[PDB]
Length: 49
DNA sequence: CGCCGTGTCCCTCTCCCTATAGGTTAGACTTTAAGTCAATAC
Image (cartoon, rainbow, N blue to C red):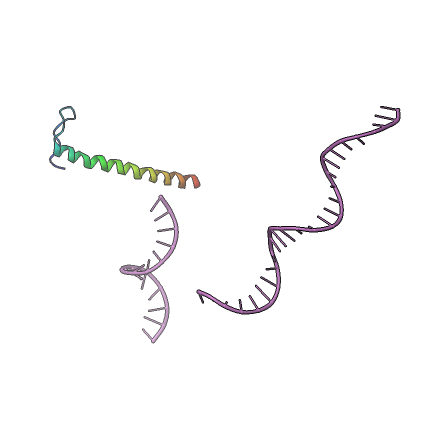
């Protein structure tokens, strides 16, 4: 996002900067959740082989 | 005229009432194993 956020968490974010941060936060959380299953399947296949 | 590669698509796997005939059980009668007492001997 080319804006970008220009406030630290000590100064306190504005409304739009926080709303922009929420994108990446939720994306990372969901990506981690799917990465667990990916790692599990890789482990199972390598164990079988 | 006669056969072979490439492409697309489909599919699969993963994360009512009546009438007859026959079998079943429940219920009571007489018999039997069972619980009981009284006298006795060592």
